[PDB]
Amino acid sequence: SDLKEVMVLNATESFVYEPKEQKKMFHATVATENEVFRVKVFNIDLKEKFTPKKIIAIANYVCRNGFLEVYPFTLVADVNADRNMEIPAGLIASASVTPKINQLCSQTKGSFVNGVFEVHKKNVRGEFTYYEIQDATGKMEVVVHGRLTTINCEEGDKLKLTCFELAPKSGNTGELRSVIHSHIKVIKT
Image 1 (tube, rainbow, N blue to C red):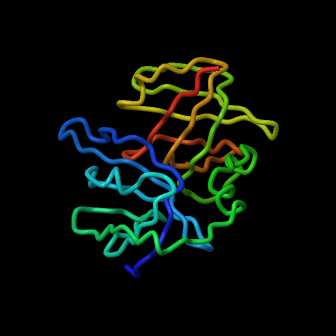
Image 2 (cartoon, rainbow, N blue to C red):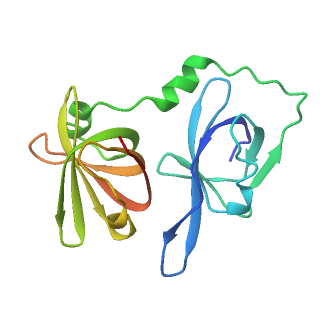
């Protein structure tokens, strides 16, 4: 847990990811001069520190699944305004790019995905809701369960997804599935 000096790019709002114990978190994206990291923050008192454009130092975090996980024992500190970090606009842009569906569904290995996807169809089956999403490269499905089945998302809207798991399937059939830390923001069109 090498210390990283980073600027905050974006953050979601705090939300309950675990309704039985009411466990809360938010997601953030941060960048060093040369690199982007996706952060899961389990101490929500840190929301202020994670304000976009702010410079912070992060140490004693946990690396899991390609995310930096921030707990109460994790150091998160303001770096002085004497810092003035140089953050390339291109790198900042690399953080906001949405993956192509044709690469996603034909993906042969599991990973965790962020992106903004337009909903072509919505099919609710029992405890699972299936969104068919489309881009210029093709279409695939996003499968939601649990708390996320209550979102209001209709055909024509867009799903801004955070930490969805790509489950590779046989036929170029891979799908995005919601997991414990998943977050959705619906963009109404």
